[PDB]
């Protein structure tokens, strides 16, 4: 969690 | 990113860049030199 993608 | 896995591709592989990866000889006009 961190949805950088 | 959290960094539990592939810390980096997710750093900019998203809407933050769209996965650039460009600039690999973009100015590589190099041929024979002289």
Image: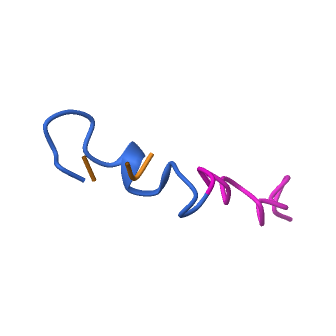
Chain colours: A orange, B blue
As drawn, is B1 to the left or to the right of B33?
left
Residue B17: image location, x then y, percent: 58, 61
Residue under the point 17% across and 49% down: B2
Residue B32: image location, x then y, percent: 84, 53
Which one is nearer the viewer's eye here, A1 or B30?
A1
Q: Which residues fall within the magenta stretch?
A: B18-34
As drawn, is A5 to the left or to the right of B23?
left
- In terms of secondary structure, what is the magenta stretch mainly? loop
Residue under the point 32% across and 49% down: B8
Instruction: Please state the total of marks drawn on the protein image.
Output: 0
Q: Is residue B22 magenta?
A: yes
Residue A3: image location, x then y, percent: 37, 48
Residue under the point 53% across and 64% down: B16
Residue B34: image location, x then y, percent: 86, 65
Residue furthest top as drawn: B5
Residue under the point 85% across and 61% down: B29
As drawn, is B16 to the left or to the right of B9?
right
Q: Is residue B9 magenta?
A: no
As drawn, is A1 to the left or to the right of A4?
left
């Amino acid at each position: 969690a961190x949805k950088x993608x | 990113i959290t960094x539990i896995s592939l810390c980096x591709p997710g750093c900019k592989x998203g809407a933050l860049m769209g996965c650039n990866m460009k600039x690999a000889x973009c100015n590589c006009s190099i041929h024979v030199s002289k």
